[PDB]
Image (cartoon, grey):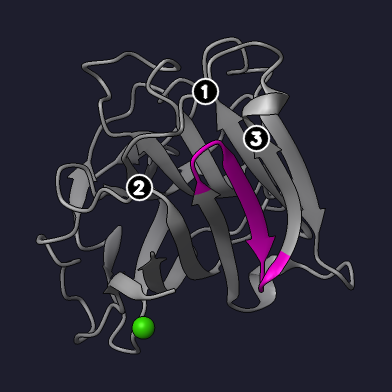
């Protein structure tokens, strides 16, 4: 193995994520899941903390609406195979939906789900002690991705500290791990005769959604603002 790319998120508090690596996606159209947040390019929703982390902040505004950030490496960093990992301290709260994931690099020239989607880590706030790893592709998408979950080995909340979420990825096979512990592997044999769409470059995405069909919506147990802290993203080949 060799570390071929990383963002270690060095820099003073309030600095922008490095534009050599990152794009901001913006908007409040639901993002395919009836999500509530408006993603912005404001330093109030994504910036470095001066302590070596990227911080994405989900906020509630005076009118009751929500803002957050969704950062991608589209057209800038496009891994194909190896180990793709991030050290992340996830937020917490009912309705909060942090994610580290990848979309096939031909999107939207190729539509979703044909483009492929690899979800490295997703969490929903009502399950603080669980993360999910998933694949979306033709015939296995949306409500029915190839998927599974990993519970914190002691049953504790993942939001308590930083954890390393990764996939190890090769032609025809993807393995998910948390803190180095592999918990599932899906291969071309698991698609039930549907095409395996993961033998191509992907780009990376970090976001915090607020609300959605799967997580449900914020309630009295949700405390805004909420931060996702990312110490680094590293790609090994
Ligand atoms: Ca760092």
Confirm whether residue 8 shows in the render.
yes
- Vertical arrangement, residue 236 with respect to residue 176, above or below: below
Locate residue 150, reporting x and y percent.
Answer: 78, 54
Q: Of helix, strand and loop, which mostly describes the magenta segment?
A: strand
Quarter of image, res 180: bottom right
Specify start and end residues of the magenta stretch as a single range: 170-181
> Does any atom of ligand 1 lie closer than 8 Å to the CB of label 1?
no
Please give the residue where the numbered disc 2 appears in the rendered image: 80
Point out the tag, 2 or 1, that comes first from the N-terminus: 1
- Vertical arrangement, residue 74 with respect to residue 33, above or below: below
What's the CA distance linking mark 2 and mark 1? 27 Å
Residue lying furthest right in this view? 154
Please give the residue where the numbered disc 3 appears in the rendered image: 187
Quarter of image, res 25: top left
If the image is split into quadrants, where does the N terminus sit?
Answer: bottom left
Q: Are marks 3 and 1 in contact (CB under 8 Å)?
A: no
What's the CA distance linking mark 2 and mark 3? 16 Å
Label 2: which secondary element? loop
The numbered mark at residue 33 is 1
Locate residue 165, reporting x and y percent.
Answer: 58, 63
> Does any atom of ligand 1 lie closer than 8 Å to the CB of label 2?
no
């Amino acid at each position: 193995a060799t570390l071929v790319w990383s963002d270690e998120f060095d820099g003073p508090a309030g600095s922008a994520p490095d534009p050599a690596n990152w794009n901001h996606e913006t908007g409040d159209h639901g993002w395919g899941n009836n999500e509530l947040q408006n993603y912005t390019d404001s330093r109030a929703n994504s910036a470095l903390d001066g302590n070596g982390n990227l911080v994405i902040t989900a906020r509630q505004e005076a009118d009751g609406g929500y803002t957050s950030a969704r950062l991608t490496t589209q057209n800038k960093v496009q891994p194909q195979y190896g180990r793709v990992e991030a050290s992340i301290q996830i937020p917490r709260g009912q309705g909060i939906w942090p994610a580290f994931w990848m979309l096939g690099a031909d999107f939207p020239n190729t539509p979703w789900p044909d483009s492929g989607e690899i979800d490295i880590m997703e969490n929903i706030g009502r399950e603080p002690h669980l993360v999910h790893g998933s694949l979306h592709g033709p015939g296995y998408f949306g409500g029915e991705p190839l998927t599974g979950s990993y519970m914190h080995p002691q049953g504790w909340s993942f939001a308590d500290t930083f954890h390393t979420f990764a996939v190890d990825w090769r032609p025809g096979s993807i393995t998910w791990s948390v803190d180095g512990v592999a918990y599932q592997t899906y291969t071309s044999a698991d698609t039930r005769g549907n095409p395996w769409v993961f033998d191509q470059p992907f780009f990376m995405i970090l976001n915090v959604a607020v609300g959605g069909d799967w997580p449900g919506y914020p309630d009295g147990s949700t405390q805004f603002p909420q931060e996702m802290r990312v110490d680094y993203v590293r790609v090994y080949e």
